Image (tube, rainbow, N blue to C red):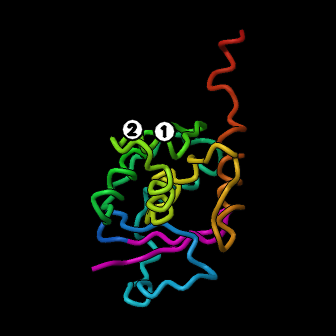
Amino acid sequence: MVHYRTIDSPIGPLTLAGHGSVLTNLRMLEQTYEPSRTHWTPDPGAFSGAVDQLNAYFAGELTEFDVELDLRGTDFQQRVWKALLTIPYGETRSYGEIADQIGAPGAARAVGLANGHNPIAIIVPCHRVIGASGKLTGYGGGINRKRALLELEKSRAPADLTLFD
């Protein structure tokens, strides 16, 4: 059983969906074919916390999420998504680095494919992974969404101006 809520965002309407307070999905679903969504119940007040944190994220005021997640995918996808969760705000990794981390040296391209299937964007940070040649990927506007998120995280001001005096 699954309910959903859509919010505005600088990168487009973000659909949050899941069961109870647990997220199963977070995607900019517009202009794409998503047949699951027809089986979902709208609930304009679900995921109160996640929406606040997302809003705070986009406003620069949040860096670490505290949200309940239920990730579904293959063993290999789960390993990749788990490793994605270890990438700090404002940092990046290469696909090769991620393949090394999950114990599959040489599997950069597989990580790229699994990264593409990430059901929960932003919070599981598939945008923080980039290949050696530096080119963003993703159809349907994906490239521009990723870039937006990367530019936001890079623009982060120092955490405490008092440290300068």
Mark 2 vs mark 1, CA separation in Å: 6 Å
Q: Secondary structure at mark 1?
A: helix
**Disc 1 marks which residue?**
97
Work out whether residue 112 or residue 71 is closer to the camera in this orientation and state it.
112
The image quadrant that residue 100 belongs to is top left
Asked if residue 151 is among those painted magenta in the image, a careful observer would answer no
**On-image quarter of the N terminus:** bottom left
Label placed on residue 101: 2
Q: Secondary structure at mark 2?
A: helix
Q: Residue at x 54, y 55 (%)?
A: 54
Work out whether residue 125 or residue 96 is closer to the camera in this orientation and state it.
96
**On-image quarter of the C terminus:** top right
Three-letter amino acid code of the residue under disc 2: Gln
Work out whether residue 74 or residue 127 is closer to the camera in this orientation and state it.
74
Q: How many numbered discs, if any?
A: 2
Looking at the picture, does residue 15 appear above or below residue 11? below
Asked if residue 8 is among those painted magenta in the image, a careful observer would answer yes
Is the C-beta separation of discs 2 and 1 under 8 Å? yes
Q: Residue at x 41, y 72 (%)?
A: 17
Work out whether residue 108 or residue 70 is closer to the camera in this orientation and state it.
108
In-image side of 78 versus 51 (left or right): left
Where does the image place residue 109, in percent across and percent down from the top left? 50, 55
Magenta range: 1-17
Q: Residue at x 64, y 43 (%)?
A: 132
In-image side of 10 versus 76 (left or right): right
Where does the image place residue 142, in percent across and percent down from the top left? 65, 65
